[PDB]
Image (cartoon, coloured by chain):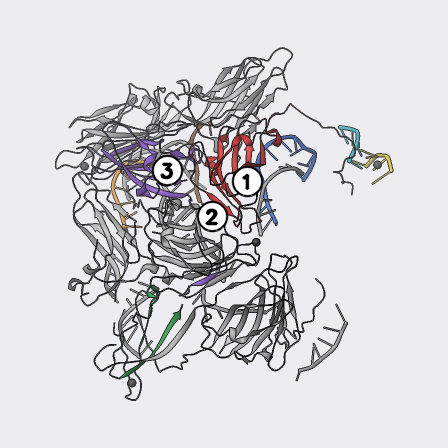
Chain colours: B green, F purple, I red, Q orange, R brown, T yellow, V blue, W cyan
Amino acid sequence: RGKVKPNRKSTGDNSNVVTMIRAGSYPKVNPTPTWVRAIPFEVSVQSGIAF
Amino acid sequence: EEFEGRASNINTRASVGYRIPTNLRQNTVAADNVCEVRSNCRQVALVISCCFN
Amino acid sequence: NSNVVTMIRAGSYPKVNPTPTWVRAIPFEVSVQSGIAFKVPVGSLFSANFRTDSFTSVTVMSVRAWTQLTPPVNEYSFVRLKPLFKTGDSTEEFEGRASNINTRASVGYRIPTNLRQNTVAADNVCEVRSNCRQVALVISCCFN
Amino acid sequence: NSNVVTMIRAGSYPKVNPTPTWVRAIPFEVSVQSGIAFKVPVGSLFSANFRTDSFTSVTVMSVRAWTQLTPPVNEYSFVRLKPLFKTGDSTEEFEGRASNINTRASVGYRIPTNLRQNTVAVDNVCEVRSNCRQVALVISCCFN
Amino acid sequence: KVPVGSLFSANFRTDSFTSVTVMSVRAWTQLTPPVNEYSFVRLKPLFKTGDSTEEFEGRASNINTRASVGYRIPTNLRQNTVAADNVCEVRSNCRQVALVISCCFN
Amino acid sequence: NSNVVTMIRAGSYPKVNPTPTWVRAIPFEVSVQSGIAFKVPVGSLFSANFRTDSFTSVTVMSVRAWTQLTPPVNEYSFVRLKPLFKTGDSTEEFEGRASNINTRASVGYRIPTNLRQNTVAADNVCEVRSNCRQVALVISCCFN
Amino acid sequence: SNVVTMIRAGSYPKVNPTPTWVRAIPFEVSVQSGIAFKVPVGSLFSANFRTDSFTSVTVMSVRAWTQLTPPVNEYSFVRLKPLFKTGDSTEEFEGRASNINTRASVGYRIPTNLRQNTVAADNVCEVRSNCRQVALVISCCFN
Amino acid sequence: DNSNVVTMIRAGSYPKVNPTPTWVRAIPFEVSVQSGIAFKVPVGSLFSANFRTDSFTSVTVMSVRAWTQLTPPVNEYSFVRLKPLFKTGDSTEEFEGRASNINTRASVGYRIPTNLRQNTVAADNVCEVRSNCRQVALVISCCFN
Amino acid sequence: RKSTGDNSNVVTMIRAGSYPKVNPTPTWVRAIPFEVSVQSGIAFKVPVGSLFSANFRTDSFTSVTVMSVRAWTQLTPPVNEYSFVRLKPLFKTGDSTEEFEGRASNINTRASVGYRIPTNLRQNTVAADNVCEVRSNCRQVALVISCCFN
RNA sequence: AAAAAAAA
RNA sequence: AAAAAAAAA
RNA sequence: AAAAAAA
RNA sequence: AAAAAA
RNA sequence: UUUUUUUUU
RNA sequence: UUUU
RNA sequence: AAAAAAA
RNA sequence: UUUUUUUU
RNA sequence: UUUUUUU
RNA sequence: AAAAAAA
RNA sequence: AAAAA
RNA sequence: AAAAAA
RNA sequence: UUUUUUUUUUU
RNA sequence: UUUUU
Ligand SMILES: [Cl-]
Ligand SMILES: [Cl-]
Ligand SMILES: [Mg+2]
Ligand SMILES: [Mg+2]
């Protein structure tokens, strides 16, 4: 391989500094994606009629 | 269908739901309706599980 | 599977939240001048074009940058990123250069968990430096 | 293997259908302008150039796009795809950008099984946005 | 054109339903074919999102025997239909066709 | 699968074909005269009623025949098939009879791989002899 | 079983009064010195082979033997050049005799892709030899 | 894959050849039968250009099968009987088959044992055929030589 | 110990027997590369006679069994366009209506595509015959044909 | 199961 | 359910 | 295996 | 099998 | 794995 | 348990 | 790839 | 191994 | 996965 | 051993 | 069990 | 085997 | 990281 | 390897 550019990522899952991300080609993007949600809202009913 | 639930305690809410099968899961715009709600109470709370797209 | 509606034997009313969090990967562009750094504003993430205009704060996790336009004549594209923090800006210049003049230059940096706090629209994400006039950004963040 | 004809001990007249279905990937081009979306019509799939002039309906499964012409000067190619449905058009903008100016920009989306209904010539598949003047489309569908 | 309204009837206990999801449609010739002919029956599925062009045909190998054929509706096309809608077209050399439609009333 | 559209990370433009092949079974009927053989034309396969009017050649793999109408009085139905080729016509008479007067008479033959060349509309498939005046055919072939 | 037994026959089966029959047809041809002779396919259809009821045949392999003695001081040889309607070949499969009193043999096999039918007007192959006659054995499928 | 060109065969000495070999066949042909009368099936019916067998003068019959070719009389069911005949001695068996449906053919057959599988020339008779149908279809598994 | 021998330094004798079966003009499997001129919107029929040439050592053949055809664009495409190429197989028993198309995802990169002929359609073709039609936005296309000369 | 001819 | 067509992402 | 049905 | 990521 | 052709319980 |  | 089954 | 038999 | 009849 | 090719 | 580096 | 540390 | 044909010693 | 039954 080679030698180092010192990004001190301590123990991998426990770094306390910013670490360089070796990015590549521009990915597939979507600024307006989907969203699965559970929407809570109230509706008003009368006694004997449907709504 | 009239999927109905009744509260066994006068102080407790009455609950009931229904699941939509996969063959009937298309899109619905604002002008559309979801379901008809009937109750002896003046207001009903709804929690709708859905996918926004 | 089932072809008709089925009853859901629901119980007590559950814990709800009409305005939940959202983990996203926001793509947007910024203009970059030659020899000048551009402080990427956090407010660029809050927009109706990203469905995030309902938020006021966001937790940035990683930042990635690509060159959006062609470099000057005879040069290879490059891009730099300097992480900015309200508790103290950094001095790293995570630089990425292209090996083909016709190809973009990409680079990024990951924010440590200890430096993942909320940021408002007035704040800035990072400084960007490039020989190209535009930089394509994709920021992995947490809207709350 | 053999070298001459062989007799087939046939039985009752089977179930026949002179006009069956056909799963295809239809390649055709559309003209796109800068900053404006083009609604790709489903009628483009029905033509004698695709052996589908006998079908009146089709079930689209997945749509893929490719920039068919070169991007403007100093820019990289991109292409957006907004899925359209008769029960409700979407707002997604699946976008793919080219990392090389001389290379196409590719993106695509898959229609879920719950949304795979028939579409006639009057209907539209998706909106296509691109900085390139034309876009190549390969639509995996089921003609019926 | 076979109307969906033929499914909502008191003769089937279904006069309380207004919509139905059809799963599979199969048809049998109900009367004898013309002279010198073997029976046949065709079915062209119809949908509100797009009519089809398939002619699922079945023929009888015996002139005294019915001709039968059917088609299955995929899960992605199993939506509701009301009385104003049509299930499919029917073509045959016989003057009546018996249909046994497997559906889900809701 | 899911209930919403998903993004496809498409790559380079694929190798496409707008007019592909199609293997089918084509049901079509022919009229036969008493004591007279009838040559089956290959042009009967190419038709808008079979979605094959876009093809000009076809490779036939097998032929199957049924008596379409009733036989003469006191007789049981029979049908013969003599294969034909442009390199040389055959003399085989693959004959099938009915054991019940009301039942169709059926027979079929298979073409070996070495004899599976293309045939145009001007060519002929086989000869059909029968005491009935109509014979139904279901030919398994490859349109190209 | 030394007596007739009863066969419980069922429905009328599929019949074919004129089947295909696979054969190995032997015949001879006259050859001149230096001249190549085209072997006609029509020789395969003859009452001497029980094949006068056939009009087509699918050839699979051809084998050749010298039928007469070679010229003086020479050893027998024979060459075969395959011929097709889609295009003639230029191969000359040759076999020579290591004994002057012994025949010479050679043969070629027709691959599956080239095993189409041939009528009487066609030709099988070209034959060259120093002997004035050649004996051919053609493994073919009549139909 | 398969070979796509002509390939040389390394043939040797001239082999044993035979231009007029034998042929195991199943010959279909029809015969006309009257009511209450038995029709002797001639062996010469097997030798014809319609069967590619006019070059054979002898044949060794192995088994015979019959089917009624025409409809039976009114209100009756089809039947057919077969009586094996040999030059060394005619049998007296009447292998009969009846149709359980008036619209269906009647069928029956008989197998010849290897000891009785000699040759028969055109002037010989295979069997006798009785039936209430005016025509019978015959399928004879035999070995031509 | 003493059994090492496959590297000969001198001539050795060959104990030959009877005269073998010989063929002075045998077959040959090849991959013939050549180019053709293509016009815009016009289909060019590729002649089989292009295979029989002294430039390929195949000028002695008169027939060939084509197995597969591959095509690459030989010149640059028009301005703003990516290269493409199409192929339509042709047969003496009946021409095909398929147009196997392969485009270029890079304007500077060739466009490639090819098709394989099935065993049932691998017959001989003489010089007067044609292999396939070729369409391309480029003015020249390069071909490589895997074929069996005979 | 079946009289007849056989059969360590 | 032979080919053509998304992929186990 | 889907739907309706008892603890 | 949604949206993010050694 | 799916759409149409052929095989085999 | 009711269906094709 | 030809005769009488294919369980 | 010849003619009648025994749960599709 | 039964086998027996000429290239 | 020598002629397509394949990631 | 024979030879020739 | 650099510089930090249950 | 996997083949069709021209000769070809040796297990 | 090369030369010999
Ligand atoms: Cl300029
Ligand atoms: Cl030495
Ligand atoms: Mg309450
Ligand atoms: Mg009867």
Secondary structure found at label 3? strand
Q: Choose between B1 and I49: the one closer to the eye.
A: I49
Residue F62 visible in rendering: yes
Q: Which mark is residue F16?
A: 2
Give me the C-alpha separation between circle 1 and circle 3. Answer: 39 Å
Secondary structure found at label 1? strand
Q: Which mark is residue I141?
A: 1
Q: Which residue is labeled 3 in the image?
A: F62
Amino acid marked by disc 1: Val
* Residue I49 image position (x, y, % from top left): 54, 30
Identify the subunit bearing mark 1.
I
* Residue I3 image position (x, y, % from top left): 76, 40
Instruction: Look at 23% across and 82% down and name the residue there.
Output: A46
User: Which quadrant does the N terminus of chain F fall into?
Assistant: bottom left
How would you rate the neighbour count of disc 3 (Cα within 10 Å): few for under 14, some for 14-19, many for 20 or more?
A: many
Q: Choose between F105 and A48: the one closer to the eye.
A: A48
In the figure, is residue I117 to the left or right of B11? right
Give me the C-alpha separation between circle 2 and circle 1. Answer: 18 Å
Identify the subunit bearing mark 3.
F
* Residue B19 image position (x, y, % from top left): 33, 71
In the figure, is residue Q5 to the left or right of I79? left
Amino acid marked by disc 2: Val
How would you rate the neighbour count of disc 1 (Cα within 10 Å): few for under 14, some for 14-19, many for 20 or more?
A: many
